[PDB]
Image (cartoon, rainbow, N blue to C red):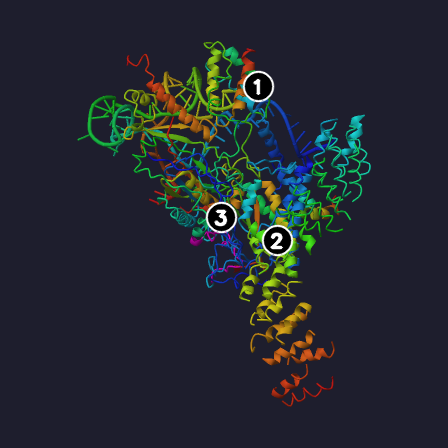
RNA sequence: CAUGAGGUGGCAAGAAAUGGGCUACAUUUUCUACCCCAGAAACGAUAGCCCUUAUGAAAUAAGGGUCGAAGGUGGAUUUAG
């Protein structure tokens, strides 16, 4: 009774302040004569005031492209600029050699724990090692299934230890000791 | 004949809502799903335990909003945020209506272990799409 | 757990905050069986 | 080289208190505690205050089941801390309260840790026996037996008199003990044996001048033991010091007894009962001193004393009377609206019949007057006689001899 | 004592102005903790006491080394590398898995 | 259990037996 | 506006990938319309492509009893989207991706991300 | 408050397979070897036999979650082939459609 | 004080016929190579026992070993496209 905000809202009034969060529909607030439903064979599609699917829409009425701009005037900060690293990544290679991944699988619902969120594969190009003229050759022969030939990239993967922050501490440790067992000369390196 | 989710034509005096007038071969063709969650996309787990909670919340609220629930609910789900939306008839006094929001909000907050927020909507009469 | 789900709904009929139609359907029907039966 | 930039640690959940600043509290709407359809929205204050209470009995009823049987709710799903519940228990069950805990004092005895813990949780005549048994079982033992006894100023200072015999609650039982030299000699005695201690030692002088010209500059709660005496942070002080020319709710009483309120307006950009006195007693100002009235009408109560000063704003300055009718309930509230149009062809005579349509559920006799200005007016004259004149003769001559049958009894019932 | 923490209670009442907008439900909801601690790292909480890639994966420090060339020790290296590839089991239950196996081959 | 339990408008239809 | 920077320089990401995974196609091309306008107001070099969908249909029996010659078959149309960002810092990404995950839609738009930080070794 | 006595025959077989799961993991880690010769591997074979019924995970028969059919079950959504089909036609699982191909 | 509940063991093999399909009865085939320019053979490959393996408290399934049956395109009749 007395349906508000829709005979009483004016234009040249700010909508991004009306729907601050994502919300459900709440048709008495929304001033559009939007319609829903597959109509009957001689009828109009359904109203706005009593629907179900305009509330079953995932509802991108929050965050209009003016709400996007007017949010980020307090969110252009938190943010410090990208270093002028002289890109195409080759001059970001001899600065920044190794490459890693650390994924999250954001689900919804009650809990957070996805056990496929500790997946760490660590990629290193071999042209960034620069201390490998024979201890290149047993790095390659130690890792059987890795080190492609068309691209000289090493991918060591760890999913043996439950936390993501220590799989990274596992990946860095097998990169450092296989490098040293490569620079370890062995007794039977000759008798081939 | 197949009788899966249709109501059957009888006369001219039987009213029916948009949803249950629609047969189940129109589920994403002409209808929406009544509950949204991240379960059935592949390969995601926690599709399984959620739907035996999803069936409670429309069997809970069929009894705690008794005689007044207009059609089925909408059970949105945003991360760790269970969003129930409901359209309900204009038959009860509003002092009762505000009671069972915060009754059911903090009893469904402390069952799912999430926050739960209710958004009611009031319609005077049951909205009828078809006089079948 | 099916006790957790089904006994909480027992007490929420007992405190009368949730009015279910199935167990209403028994205790009215069980009223009219004990008038004759049993 | 390329130098890597700064790990701008982005101040957690304040990441989205940053966004809440951008959204303004919008107009044209109810406050957000309620629901957004018109039926569940309230209309006036009595509905809205009850409704948040009606929401509140949602909580305490739902909570009660959780706390009276928690074994429905021990399925722990991750984790919020969201889950329900002769020496050792004597200090443990002193934390979960009283009378059944403190009764255990002598069956155990048949130390000073729970002699100043379990002997505090009462505040108690019979449990005052164990209060003097405190060091018969320190400083805290003998302290607030009397600071918890300025409520349960007599038997408190008498125990402050009987503690000098052999904290911040030395200065709280004795803080509000005519009496403005012992008051002097109490805060010289504070070095003998705060923003609360000084804030209690003028609460008592408030109810029972020359010490009130002195009590200040020895801060927010150090003003309500001052602002009761007269009757930015610099722009509080440039407001408050120039007021002699828990916190605010008196300052709308001074500014209503006397641009003056716009100094308070800065601290608003910095209770449910007195937070209307905030707003109702502010609207009486901005109405009196028009364009700046019409904006502030839309801003305050959309998101009986407020409509007894509402209408006379329109007196001193014309078409918004049928606008402001529908917010009366959203006789007495129905007559001062009917005062003003009796003091124009289309919009004024309609809503008086809606006051009549209000009335079917100095008042009734002023409905015929504005209506004929711009049949159904006579059936009010039928009830003026069973429950003014010079316009009834006016409307008869223009509307003729059957209306010269109307004016015949106009002098007969005089 | 009680009087220091009760002044943390009645203090909360004087500033508790209502929620008033759509954002401060989300602000309140993790100041308590029912909402998520956005951003999501999928391992929030969940520490295993500073586990760190040598307790989980080198079960040498809990072996209590026997005569190594005996057939029992080769069976313990099988069990050790099995417990190595667990992300499911923690390090307190890995040593407890050995602990039952320790009280068996002293018996047999 | 609870998950057996059902509405009324299915229950009277299964108890009245108004169609063959 | 309170941020309180410290001693410690960046973690520095490169080529953050976002796989938004949905059911309704009309949400995701309205989700990516937000995400290009959530990211090109931070000047972020961005591309979008659509991975092919995996529709995992399964079958079920129709009557409660007999009649294996009568099945009904169900399906999941579950769709995809990539939000291939490139070369952005560790502070900026985790606040850009904040505003993304805070305002991802309802049940539709499951999301998967890859994070590749670069990081000088020892 | 399980829907049959039958489910509560089977709840007992999932909790008594769970507390005795550590034991069945460690004693049956002592058989499937080539090493530790057969006398060391045959007195461990008696102890599993004297460990009871209702403990091994083979005695579970994997049942529907609310109407307790033993078969016709769908593992991903937990429920049998009828009552899952009851909800999918009112549109009550996220993204279940009729397949028309 | 049972037509309910709980425990251990057991029940599913064929004088026979019949329904549905696999394998075949082969030269458009059989074995290897290649998976489509060859070269050899001039049949059919179950079931049955035997040995390991998998999974499992505990043996059904796979693989290998041996045997190499009935089988020569099949009546009235009938099915699908
Ligand atoms: Mg059919």
Instruction: Say which residue label 3 marks.
Output: D19
Which segment is the magenta one? A44-66
Q: How crowded is mark 1: few (under 14 residues within 10 Å), some or many (20 or more)?
A: few
Instruction: Say which residue label 1 marks.
Output: H49
In the depicted structure, whether residue G3 falls above or below residue A28: above
Q: Residues within 10 Å of mark 3 (few under 14, many from 20)?
A: some
Query: Do residues under tags 2 and 3 come within 8 Å of each other at their CB atoms?
Result: no
The quarter holding residue I51 reads: top left
Query: Do residues under tags 2 and 1 come within 8 Å of each other at their CB atoms?
Result: no
Is the distance from the Cβ of mark 1 to the nearest ligand 1 atom less than 8 Å?
A: no
Separation (CA) of disc 2 from disc 1? 90 Å
Is the distance from the Cβ of mark 3 to the nearest ligand 1 atom less than 8 Å?
A: no
- The secondary structure that most of the magenta stretch takes on is loop
Mark 2 or mark 1, whichever is nearer to me:
2
Question: What element does badge 2 sit on?
Answer: helix
Q: Earlier in the sequence, mark 2 or mark 3?
A: 3
Q: In which quadrant will I find the C terminus of chain D? A: bottom right
**As rendered, which of D233 and B31 lies closer to the eye?**
D233
Separation (CA) of disc 2 from disc 3? 36 Å
Left or right position of E63 against A180: right
Mark 1 or mark 3, whichever is nearer to me:
3
Left or right position of A105 against E10: left
Residue located at (81% from left, 25% from top): D110
Q: How many labels does the image show?
A: 3
Mark 2 or mark 3, whichever is nearer to me:
2
**As rendered, which of I65 and A94 lies closer to the eye?**
A94
Instruction: Say which residue label 2 marks.
Output: D241
Q: Position of residue H44 (x, y in %)?
A: 54, 15
Subunit of mark 3?
A: D
Q: Position of residue A163 (x, y in %)?
A: 47, 30
């Amino acid at each position: 009774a007395l349906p508000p905000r829709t005979e009483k809202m004016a234009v040249d009034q700010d909508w991004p302040s009306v729907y601050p969060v994502a919300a459900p529909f709440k048709p008495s607030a929304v001033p559009l004569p939007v319609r829903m439903g597959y109509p009957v064979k001689k009828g109009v599609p359904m109203a706005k005031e009593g629907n179900l699917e305009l509330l079953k829409i995932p509802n991108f009425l929050h965050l209009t492209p003016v709400a996007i701009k007017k949010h980020c005037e307090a969110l252009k900060d938190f943010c410090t600029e990208w270093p002028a690293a002289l890109d195409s990544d080759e001059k970001c290679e001899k600065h920044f050699p190794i490459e890693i991944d650390s994924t999250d699988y954001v689900s919804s619902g009650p809990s957070v724990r996805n056990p496929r969120a500790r997946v760490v594969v660590l990629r290193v190009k071999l042209s960034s090692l620069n201390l490998d003229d024979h201890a290149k050759k047993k790095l390659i022969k130690l890792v059987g299934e890795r080190y492609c030939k068309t691209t000289d990239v090493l991918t060591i993967k760890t999913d043996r230890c439950p936390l993501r922050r220590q799989n990274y501490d596992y990946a860095v440790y097998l990169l450092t000791v296989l490098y040293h067992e490569s620079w370890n000369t062995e007794e039977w390196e000759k008798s081939k | 004949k197949n009788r899966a989710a249709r109501v059957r034509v009888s006369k001219g005096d039987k009213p029916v809502t948009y949803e249950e007038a629609h047969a189940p071969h129109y589920i994403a063709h002409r209808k929406g799903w009544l509950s949204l969650h991240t379960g059935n996309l592949d390969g995601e787990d926690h599709a399984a335990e959620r739907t035996v909670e999803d069936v409670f919340l429309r069997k809970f609220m069929w009894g705690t909003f008794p005689g007044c629930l207009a059609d089925q609910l909408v059970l949105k789900r945003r991360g760790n945020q269970l969003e129930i939306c409901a359209v309900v008839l204009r038959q009860l006094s509003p002092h009762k209506y505000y009671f069972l929001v915060g009754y059911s909000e903090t009893l469904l907050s402390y069952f799912y272990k999430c926050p739960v927020r209710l958004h009611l909507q009031t319609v005077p009469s049951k909205v009828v799409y078809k006089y079948l | 757990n099916h006790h957790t789900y089904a006994e909480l709904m027992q007490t929420l009929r007992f405190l009368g905050l949730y009015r279910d139609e199935h167990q209403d359907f028994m205790d009215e029907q069980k009223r009219l069986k004990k008038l004759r039966g049993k | 080289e390329v130098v890597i930039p700064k790990k701008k640690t982005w101040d957690k959940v304040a990441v989205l208190q940053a966004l809440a600043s951008t959204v303004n509290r919008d107009t044209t709407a109810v406050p957000y505690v309620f629901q957004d359809d018109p039926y569940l929205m309230p209309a006036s204050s009595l509905e809205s205050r009850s409704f948040l209470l009606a929401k509140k009995s949602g909580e305490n009823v739902a909570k009660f089941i959780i706390n009276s049987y928690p074994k429905y709710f021990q399925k722990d799903i991750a984790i919020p801390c969201l889950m329900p519940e002769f020496e050792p228990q004597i200090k443990d069950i002193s934390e979960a309260a009283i009378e059944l805990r403190k009764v255990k004092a002598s069956v155990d005895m048949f130390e000073e840790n729970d002699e100043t813990s379990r002997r505090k949780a009462g505040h108690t005549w019979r449990a005052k026996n164990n209060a003097e048994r405190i060091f018969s079982l320190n400083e805290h033992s003998y302290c607030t037996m009397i600071r918890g006894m300025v409520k349960h100023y007599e038997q408190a200072l008498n125990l402050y008199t009987e503690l000098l015999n052999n904290d911040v609650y030395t200065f709280n039982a004795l803080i509000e003990a005519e009496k403005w030299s012992k008051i002097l000699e109490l805060l010289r005695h504070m070095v003998a044996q705060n923003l609360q201690t000084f804030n209690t030692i003028l609460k008592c002088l408030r109810r029972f001048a020359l010490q009130v010209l002195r009590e200040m500059k020895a801060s927010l709660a150090t003003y309500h033991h001052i602002i009761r005496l007269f009757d930015l942070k610099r722009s509080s002080f440039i407001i408050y010091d120039i007021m002699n020319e828990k916190f605010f709710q008196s300052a709308m009483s001074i500014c209503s007894s006397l641009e003056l309120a716009y100094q308070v307006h800065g601290l608003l950009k910095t209770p449910d009962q007195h937070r209307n006195f905030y707003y109702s007693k502010f609207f009486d100002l901005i109405c009196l001193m028009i364009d700046v009235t019409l904006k502030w009408y839309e801003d305050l109560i959309p998101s009986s004393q407020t409509m007894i000063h509402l209408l006379q704003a329109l007196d001193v300055a014309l078409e918004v009377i049928p606008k402001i009718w529908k917010d009366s309930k959203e006789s007495d509230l129905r007559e001062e609206i009917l005062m003003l149009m009796a003091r124009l062809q289309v919009a004024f005579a309609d809503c008086a019949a809606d006051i009549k349509s209000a009335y079917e559920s100095t008042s009734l006799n002023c409905i015929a007057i504005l209506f004929l200005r711009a049949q159904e007016a006579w059936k009010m004259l039928g009830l003026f006689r069973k429950h003014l004149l010079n316009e009834l003769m006016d409307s008869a001559k223009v509307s003729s001899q059957a209306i010269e049958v109307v004016e015949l009894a106009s002098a007969f019932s005089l | 004592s009680l009087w220091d923490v009760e002044f943390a209670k009645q203090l909360a009442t004087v500033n508790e102005q209502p929620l008033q907008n759509g954002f401060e439900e989300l602000i309140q909801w993790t100041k308590e903790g029912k909402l998520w601690e956005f951003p999501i790292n999928n391992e929030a909480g969940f520490d295993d006491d500073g586990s760190e890639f040598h307790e989980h994966i080198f079960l040498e420090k809990h072996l209590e080394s026997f005569p190594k060339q005996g057939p029992i020790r080769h069976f313990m290296e099988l069990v050790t590398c099995g417990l190595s590839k667990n992300p499911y089991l923690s390090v307190k239950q890995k040593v407890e898995h050995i602990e039952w196996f320790r009280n068996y081959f002293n018996e047999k | 259990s609870f998950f057996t339990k059902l509405t009324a408008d299915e229950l009277w239809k299964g108890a009245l037996a108004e169609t063959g | 506006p309170v941020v309180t920077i410290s001693d410690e320089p960046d973690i520095l990401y490169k080529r953050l990938s976002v796989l938004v995974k949905g059911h309704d196609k009309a949400v995701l091309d309205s989700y990516e319309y937000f995400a290009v306008l959530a990211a090109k107001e931070l000047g972020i070099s961005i591309k979008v492509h659509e991975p092919p969908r995996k529709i995992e249909r399964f079958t079920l029996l129709q009557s409660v009893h007999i009649y294996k010659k009568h099945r009904v078959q169900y399906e999941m149309r579950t769709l995809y989207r990539c939000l291939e960002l490139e070369h952005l810092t560790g502070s900026t990404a985790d606040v850009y991706l904040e505003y993304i995950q805070r305002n991802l839609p309802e049940g539709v738009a499951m999301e998967v991300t890859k994070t590749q930080l670069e990081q000088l070794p020892e | 408050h399980y829907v049959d006595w039958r489910m509560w025959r089977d709840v007992k077989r999932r909790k008594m397979a769970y507390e005795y799961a550590d034991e069945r993991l460690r004693i049956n880690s002592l058989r499937k070897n080539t090493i530790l010769p057969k006398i060391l591997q045959d007195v461990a074979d008696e102890e599993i036999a004297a460990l009871p019924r209702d403990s091994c995970p083979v005695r579970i028969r994997n049942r529907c979650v609310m109407t307790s059919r033993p078969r016709g079950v769908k593992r991903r959504w937990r429920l049998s082939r009828i009552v899952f089909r009851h909800l999918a036609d009112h549109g009550q699982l996220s993204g279940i459609q009729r397949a028309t191909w």
